[PDB]
């Protein structure tokens, strides 16, 4: 059973977008389909639901044409139109199939999600800068390295170290927004013998802006 | 509509422990359902109809209650148990979810491993200077940070950002980043990073001089 | 009597081969006959549709020829009954029930051609009557006919071949084998004493008539409603309530059907000509309404699939109900040949749908589909007026094929029987046998 | 005549107290059936858990499989031989007698004897159904509430005895209709008129089914999915299959009856030779429920597998023979538990077999053995116990393949017609006849 | 109800091709599917059949793995793999849904068929040349135009006129084969008071190469 | 496997005629079928189980027979009935089709509309010289094409192509293609197209001039 919803991204305030959830691994009819969104760092909220015969569609206590849920049983996919988008809709959108036990209904199987950002801000590539320790720091047991991915929009960037291979002791911090741009940094702690006598590289991908960048962390001469 | 309010917002508890989170309705509810949301993945169905364990769920889990008050319980809490639990009713329409209960692995105290960094040369080749300072691997999550440009305290252009709890040691890591203009930065020399944790009374300083 | 039981147990389920073999030939005939009748009715409804095309312009002339066709064919039916076999008026199930109690004659030489050609007229005119009436009675008489023609002696042979005829009668009428056999052993049989009806032979009879029905009516169901949704456990109580509503209405309808027999008896006073013409007036009203609002007229089988899918509005349902109550009465209570079984399914669906709609908006957390309440309500009027729930529930199940709705169906039905009991209503088939059986003593 | 007009106007008028009490009966029967069901499950489960704890040493596991099923079998035969010999075997024969007033309904004894006795024989993985236990327990439950509330009259005595048996079969197969239909085709006094209120039988069955759905929702007992259809030129094949069930129905009755006799000598009516012989059979069940589970158990597990045609011809023939054996040894040894279920199992396995031969013989019919499997399922019930209308409706309710209704009726009726003309008897009457005759002899 | 079989075209003798049939409008389970073929200018031959759960699959008197009929019910699609392809397999392949009356089965709804040509030759887009009347056209009531489709392989092509809005008054002559290449032309009579006054275009479509050519008949100036 | 062979391989009849074609089988077949395949179209289940008509087949069609011999009758044939009809059994595996009876319509006379076409300008950018001549809508089907380059008769590389009988008008049509090299066409001037048909004693002629 897979519910794979696409469509999320960056839209402008006042605009609109068509989220889509594509279904696999069960009879898509018979099943009620529902949209549920999660405002970042906040509770889950119910958008709406549609029945197999698309003859009952229930939305949350919400303005007249805001949401427009429909399904195309023939393509086994569930759609959500949001109109007049505003910064309140900036959230992670999940589609779900509905079931029951005694008959008090529950959200059976969820999907992965897609993220909608509602901002007037412009898509902007990131600047990747290495974070080699200074000519002042003593090479202890562990040596902390890092790189700073500053000044991009919107989320996400994907920071992985040594083409993924260095999977231990890594901390990709959450990004923070300021004056319409995100900034995050990522740490990798190799042992003292590991560096600089070996190549440590950070790979930053911001797919939002077609940016794939590799930044070598060379020591401070 | 019905408002469910999950009582412990955030909570920590050691492995092998009786953990219990409330879900108090603002009205009359029947047969609620619980959802486990691990960090960065689909909310999965845990408990349903006030008490029933779904296919896959280890038996250490169980819910109950009625009327206006329900609760999920863990007898022997394992490692793979710390996530966010979301109660949800659909006895009264429109359905509602709880605020969530964030369960976290409690552990032995750990003092922060501090690393301070000088703005890269390429960033300066732009007129920006960012002083990154890492505070890595510490329990509990509570920590204080404070910058010292030329031995003098600084509060502008500082941004701090904690990771969520780790699952390779259940610690935290927070990064403080002070940003200045190439000029702003260049008329100063001594750059200190001060970390005030519960593990000490005198802070772990880490600094560097431009010269 | 214990030693007698050991004697009997060791001798249970032993029907004489001749009774079994004759049950087979009963079914075969009943079926072919039902099939023939079915086709006759179809052909006539079709010719009548062909006339309205020949006068598709002139609006009043259309409304005229719709009336006159259904008038003439109705008159022809009332006549064939009033003149040659008055016992074959109305349903016919009351009479065959009597015939099993030895309280009524099975004058097949009369009824067979009267009911057959008479029904052909009333049904083929688009009157609000079923086919069960015609086929069940015709079925019994056919079983009587082969009892006489082969001079089979004994109570067993007389009740059995009379019963299996009725069973193969209902069976070839609804493509419902089980409903036929169940109908006999819940309603048709002498209800107060032990009888010599061989169940195994009833079956063989039903089988044969179903096979005869499938030979000619393969690959098109009578009612297609598709597979509906499920019913969750916390929904069930709503089916009880629905049943209660059918329960209080069941006897109320029986008053109307009985009383309307009386009220219409005065319009003619037992006079052949006042009757025949009154009949042609009702009949013509049906072919008329089968043009200006076909939902009000006809057998009813057409509006069922439409109602279940929720394609009717609340208004249209209420209107369909009211107007069907009217036209169902006027046709049946006027003693025209034809069952009431079918239009009772129609009325049950239409009510169930309505209750389902109200249910749907009141409880959106149940995720209701009115059509489940339409299917629960289908056999409910049968369980509240005719008081044969086990027949009505299995009748529905066999036609709609929604076994997942078995519980709501039973619960609604049982609620309808329990409330039709506590509001002092009577099995409408007994009630008419009692009126007929009492009216024959009350002239001595 | 004037008596009839008096009766007609007074038909279907059951005293509210009979109705009300039928409702309580069902409720209890159901909850009990549910409880028993869960008990058997729990025990089958513990026994599975023991075989895990000795999952290495091969003969050690084969032993612990025997010993578990032996011990729980012995426990069952004992509880029966010691405190209620009337609750041995099925129990349906007895309750039929009870409705004829020819047998006593000693509920104070049978209820806990059948219950905990069945728990032992069933939970040991013996080839017995749940019907036996639930139907009898059901009747006794209806007797218990008749006594405890002191309800007077024939109607109250037969009705509450019947609805108990009905709600008994109902919560046994999640089959409401099969329950009601079984009463009015088999359970009722077959030769005289009775005072059983159908309306009240319903209410009872309803309640027990609601009790069953409350604890067993969202999992069918048999899931076979929607099979294909049956074209009209295929029908004769179901007649032939029925005829084959018709000749075998009585032959099976001989072996079930005869095997009661041949097993009665091994103990001679002796409690100790009996209980030990019972533990020997029981232990053979838990053993075979490991080395070829298809030969052992209630049978419900092999049905879906058989219908889908996942068994080979060999495997089918072997599962048949071995099940004939194990079904006899367990029921004919008078262990508590129905024969209803393993009879469905036998019917499916034969039907499937017939269907396979059919498939290769007539490729132009486009057959699917699984249709013959579902036609054959209720067929042994229509040939041995000679209740086809209950067997057909029982299968229909469990398999949900209504488009196969004609094949199902044709096979069934062919089985009843040929079990009559080969001199066989309703196996539930034959046992009542044996028991009622052995009482005066 | 439509069976829309594709995948046919050119094969080199001895190789193998997979035909697909895509169905839509009926529960694709519940039905036995079949394959019937038609060699050019000849009758009908039964390839094979297959039930719903792919548990019975009969073929005609063929060989080892000569034909192989599969079906992906999840895609509503029927497949046919023909291997070791000799030139008796140069035919038109109908996928057909099977059904019975009394019981003796028939082929119910038939597909359009795909064309399979077994030859060593090369796949070639056709050239489309507009046939207009010479400057000395004594244009009476109805003008006759056409277009010449020459130099394509294999079969077939389809000609429509003005995307087929012009149905009446069209002929398309059967292709004649010369030098291992095909050539046909289509004719279209229309009112003189309708050309050159309006747009008259021929739509030539050769699927084997995936080529449409839309030649527009321009009056000879 | 049963071999079905069909009575007339090809038959001709004027509409209003009663028409029967026959399907004869090697053994015993029961409840056969019939398909209609009108020109350049996939077959249509026409008659089934020996006598039933598929939904939407005129009541002018009937079908009967048993054992070895079967028929299909068009009682008062219509001109729109021009197809090839196939019988098919599956009373014995594997199913087998018939050879096909091909119904042709006899209609009244119908003189041909001739149209001649000069090689297009782009075809000349390719050294080709295909002169086209359509002879459309004629009955009967016998027509004779004749090419006269500069009055002089030509017969090298002239190819003909006839359509089937049309479904509604019952008339045939024919195209003719005189194909040459670039200079081969340019080294002449007067191209004619000659068509002699039952409908006219003296041939129908159409021609174009390069100059
Ligand atoms: Br009547
Ligand atoms: Br009736
Ligand atoms: Br027994
Ligand atoms: Br039993």
Image (cartoon, coloured by chain):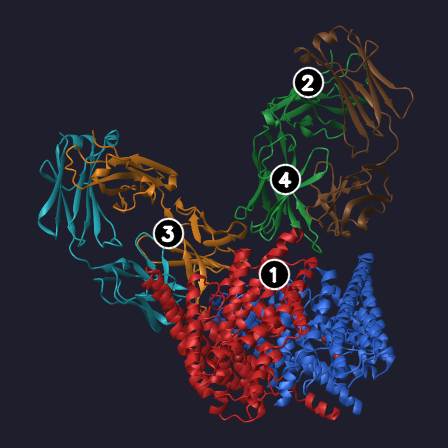
Chain colours: A green, B brown, C red, D blue, E orange, F cyan
Task: State the image coordinates of residue C57 (x, y, percent, origin top left).
Answer: 32, 59
> Residue D321, how many percent across, how many down?
67, 73
Counting from the top left corner in percent of width and height, residue F40 is at: 32, 51
Among the 4 quarters of the image, the one containing residue B37: top right
> Can you identify the residue that label 3 sits on?
E92
Task: Name the image quarter holding the C terminus of chain F.
Answer: top left
**Crowding at mark 3 (Cα within 10 Å: few <14, some 14-19, many 20+):** many
**As drawn, is E138 to the left or to the right of D402?**
left
Does the Cβ of the disc 1 residue fall within 8 Å of ligand 2? Answer: no
Report in which chain the residue with disc 3 lies. E
For residue A129, the mark is 2
Is D284 in front, or is B106?
Answer: B106
Residue under numbered circle 1? C373
Badge nearest the viewer, 4 or 2: 4
Viewer-nearest of discs 3 and 2: 2
Q: Visible in this render: residue F99?
A: yes
Label 4 neighbourhood size at 10 Å, few (<14), some (14-19), many (20+)? few
Q: Nearer the viewer, mark 2 or mark 1?
A: 1
Question: Is the residue marked by circle 2 packed among few (<14), some (14-19), or many (20+) residues within 10 Å?
Answer: many
Helix, strand or loop at label 2? It is strand
Foreground residue among D434 and C214 = C214
Element type where label 1 sits in the image: helix
Please state which of the two labelled residues, at mark 3 or mark 1, is closer to the viewer: 1
- Left or right of C329, for residue C113: left
Label 3 vs label 2: CA separation?
65 Å
Q: Label 4 belongs to which residue? A: A62
């Amino acid at each position: 059973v897979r519910l794979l919803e696409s469509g999320g991204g960056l839209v402008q305030p006042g605009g609109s977008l068509k989220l889509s959830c594509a279904a696999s691994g069960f009879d898509y009819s018979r099943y009620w389909m529902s949209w549920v969104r999660q405002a970042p760092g906040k509770g889950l909220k119910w958008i709406g639901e549609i029945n197999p015969v698309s003859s009952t569609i229930n939305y949350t206590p919400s303005l007249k044409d805001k949401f427009i849920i429909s399904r195309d049983n023939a393509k086994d996919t569930l759609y959500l139109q949001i109109s007049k988008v505003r910064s309140e809709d900036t959230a992670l959108y999940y589609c779900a199939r509905l079931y029951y036990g005694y008959g008090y209904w529950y959200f059976d199987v969820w999907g992965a999600g897609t993220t909608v950002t509602v901002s007037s801000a412009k898509t902007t590539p990131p600047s990747v800068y290495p974070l080699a320790p200074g000519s002042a720091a003593a090479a202890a047991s562990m040596v902390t390295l890092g790189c700073l991915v500053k000044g991009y929009f919107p989320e996400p960037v994907t920071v992985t170290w040594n083409s993924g291979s260095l999977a231990a002791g890594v901390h990709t911090f959450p990004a923070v927004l300021q004056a319409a741009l995100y900034t995050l940094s990522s740490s990798v702690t190799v042992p003292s013998s590991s560096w600089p006598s070996e190549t440590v590289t950070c790979n930053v991908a911001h797919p939002a802006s077609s940016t794939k960048v590799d930044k070598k962390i060379v020591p401070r001469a | 509509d019905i408002v469910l309010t999950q009582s412990p917002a955030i909570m920590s508890a050691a492995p092998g422990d009786k953990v219990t989170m409330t879900c108090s309705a603002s009205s009359s509810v029947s047969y609620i359902h619980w959802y486990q949301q691990k960090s960065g993945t689909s909310p999965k169905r845990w408990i349903y109809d006030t008490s029933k364990l779904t296919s896959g769920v280890p038996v250490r889990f169980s819910g109950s209650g009625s009327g206006t008050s329900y609760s999920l319980t863990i007898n022997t809490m394992e490692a793979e148990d710390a996530a966010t639990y979301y109660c949800q009713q659909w006895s009264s329409h429109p359905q509602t979810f709880g605020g969530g209960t964030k369960l976290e692995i409690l552990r032995a105290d750990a003092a922060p491993t501090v690393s301070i960094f000088p703005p890269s040369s390429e960033q300066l080749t732009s007129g920006g200077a960012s002083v990154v300072c890492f505070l890595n691997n510490f329990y509990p999550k509570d920590i204080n940070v404070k910058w010292k440009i030329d031995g003098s305290e600084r509060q502008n252009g500082v941004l701090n950002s904690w990771t969520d709890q780790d699952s390779k040691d259940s610690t935290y890591s927070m990064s403080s980043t002070l940003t200045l203009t190439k000029d702003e930065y260049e008329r100063h020399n001594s750059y200190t990073c001060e970390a005030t944790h519960k593990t000490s009374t005198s802070p772990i300083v880490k600094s560097f001089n431009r010269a | 009597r214990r030693r007698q039981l050991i004697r009997q147990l060791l001798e249970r389920d032993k029907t004489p081969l001749a009774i079994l073999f004759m049950a087979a030939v009963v079914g075969t005939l009943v079926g072919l006959a039902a099939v023939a009748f079915d086709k006759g009715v179809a052909w006539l409804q079709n010719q009548r549709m062909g006339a309205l095309v020949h006068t598709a312009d002139n609006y009043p002339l259309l409304l005229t020829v719709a009336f006159l066709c259904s008038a003439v064919l109705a008159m022809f039916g009332y006549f064939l009954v009033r003149k040659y076999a008055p016992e074959a008026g109305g349903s016919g199930i009351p009479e065959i029930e009597g015939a099993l109690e030895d309280q009524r004659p099975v004058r097949w030489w009369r009824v067979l051609p009267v009911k057959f050609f008479g029904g052909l007229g009333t049904l083929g005119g688009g009157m609000v009557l079923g086919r069960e009436g015609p086929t069940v009675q015709i079925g019994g008489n056919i079983g009587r006919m082969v009892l006489d023609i082969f001079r089979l002696k004994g109570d067993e042979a007389r009740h059995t071949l009379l019963a299996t005829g009725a069973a193969a009668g209902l069976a070839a009428a609804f493509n419902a084998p089980l409903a036929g056999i169940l109908f006999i052993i819940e309603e048709m049989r002498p209800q107060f004493r032990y009888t010599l009806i061989s169940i195994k032979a009833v079956f063989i009879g039903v089988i044969m008539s179903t096979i005869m029905y499938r030979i000619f009516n393969h690959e098109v169901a009578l009612i297609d409603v598709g597979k509906l949704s499920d019913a969750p456990l916390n929904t069930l109580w709503l089916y009880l309530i629905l049943g209660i509503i059918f329960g209080i209405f069941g006897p109320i309808f029986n008053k109307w059907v009985l009383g309307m027999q009386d009220l219409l008896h005065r319009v003619h006073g037992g006079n052949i000509t006042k009757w025949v013409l009154m009949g042609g007036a009702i009949g013509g009203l049906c072919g008329l309404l089968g043009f200006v609002a076909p939902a009000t007229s006809g057998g009813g089988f057409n509006l069922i699939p439409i109602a279940t899918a929720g394609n009717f509005s609340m208004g249209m349902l209420v209107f369909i109900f009211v107007a069907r109550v009217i036209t169902t009465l006027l046709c049946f209570s006027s003693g025209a040949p034809g069952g009431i079984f079918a239009p009772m399914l129609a009325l049950g669906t239409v009510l169930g749908t309505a209750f389902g709609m109200v249910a749907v908006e009141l409880f959106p957390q149940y995720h209701l589909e009115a059509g489940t309440f339409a299917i629960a309500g289908m056999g409910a009027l049968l369980a509240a007026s005719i008081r044969a729930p086990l027949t009505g529930i299995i009748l529905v199940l066999e036609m709609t094929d929604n076994y997942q709705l078995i519980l709501p169906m039973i619960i609604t039905g049982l609620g309808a029987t329990l409330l039709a009991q506590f509001t002092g209503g009577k099995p409408l088939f007994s009630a008419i046998l009692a009126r007929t059986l009492a009216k024959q003593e009350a002239e001595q």
